[PDB]
Amino acid sequence: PSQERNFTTAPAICHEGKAYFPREGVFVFNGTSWFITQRNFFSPQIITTDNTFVSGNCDVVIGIINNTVYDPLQPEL
Amino acid sequence: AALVSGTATAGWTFGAGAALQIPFAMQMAYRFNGIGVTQNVLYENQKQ
Ligand SMILES: *[C@@H]1O[C@H](CO)[C@@H](O[C@@H]2O[C@H](CO)[C@@H](O[C@@H]3O[C@H](CO[C@H]4O[C@H](CO)[C@@H](O)[C@H](O)[C@@H]4O)[C@@H](O)[C@H](O[C@H]4O[C@H](CO)[C@@H](O)[C@H](O)[C@@H]4O)[C@@H]3O)[C@H](O)[C@H]2NC(C)=O)[C@H](O)[C@H]1NC(C)=O
Ligand SMILES: *[C@@H]1O[C@H](CO)[C@@H](O[C@@H]2O[C@H](CO)[C@@H](O[C@@H]3O[C@H](CO[C@H]4O[C@H](CO)[C@@H](O)[C@H](O)[C@@H]4O)[C@@H](O)[C@H](O)[C@@H]3O)[C@H](O)[C@H]2NC(C)=O)[C@H](O)[C@H]1NC(C)=O
Ligand SMILES: *[C@@H]1O[C@H](CO)[C@@H](O[C@@H]2O[C@H](CO)[C@@H](O[C@@H]3O[C@H](CO)[C@@H](O)[C@H](O)[C@@H]3O)[C@H](O)[C@H]2NC(C)=O)[C@H](O)[C@H]1NC(C)=O
Image (cartoon, rainbow over all chains, first blue to last red; front, side, top):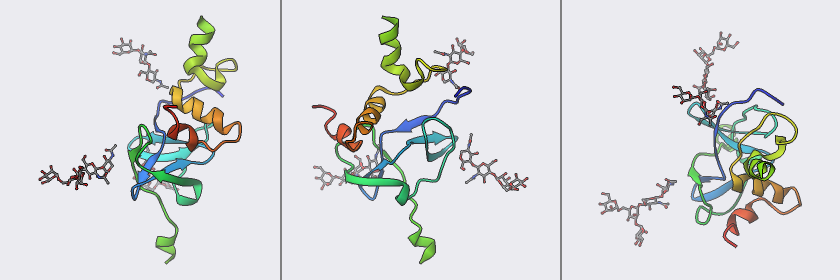
């Protein structure tokens, strides 16, 4: 790996009061938008329910920030 | 001293390629997942 970029990150994101954690990747803040991607290659993906997980509330996670989570149910319904 | 200082923030590419900077806690959280304990456990028990 070589040429890189600076991004802002977050341990977790808070949505509906719940603490959402990433699966295999890390949360990344680009030019005014949050995505999720693998550490070894910057390829940003939309943050969706199925690509993250939730456990515990937004209570004890240090540095947790507010965000939204996409749920296919909405356009599917 | 240089090695230790480096690894403290440099992470996985430290001895492989270009230096990167990763927040300490983030690095640790990953290494825990690397063992087989769900990542969130570290944050919740970060103090302990
Ligand atoms: C992610 O997003 C969430 C949601 O916004 C943020 O959490 C909120 O943080 C705010 C600020 O601390 C909490 O504010 C609540 O305001 C209520 C309204 O009263 C205030 O505002 C009116 C406006 O006119 C004033 O007139 C009034 O004098 C007050 O200034 C309060 O009632 C809430 O009080 C709660 O806690 C006390 C604790 O003893 C209880 O007694 C109350 O009954 C009540 O429970 C509170 O102050 C807001 O509640 C928070 N929401 C949640 C869900 O936590 C996160 O901070 C944000 N994350 C980041 C990183 O910014
Ligand atoms: C941070 O993430 C943000 C959210 O994804 C990024 O915002 C996006 O920025 C791009 C700019 O490249 C906008 O693209 C728009 O695309 C439409 C469609 O036409 C274009 O694509 C067709 C495909 O074949 C191509 O043929 C055309 O020539 C165009 O290339 C254009 O009409 C718009 O003018 C614009 O190009 C995204 O829409 C925009 N997303 C949102 C939600 O606004 C942001 O850029 C990212 N920042 C960084 C630094 O990466
Ligand atoms: C990620 O951000 C860091 C800083 O938070 C970048 O490092 C800094 O980059 C600047 C510009 O490349 C370096 O030079 C500085 O230029 C300004 C211009 O006026 C000057 O005033 C400063 O005195 C300095 O010369 C700066 O030294 C550098 N700092 C460090 C510690 O590296 C970094 O390059 C960014 N990385 C990416 C991939 O964008």
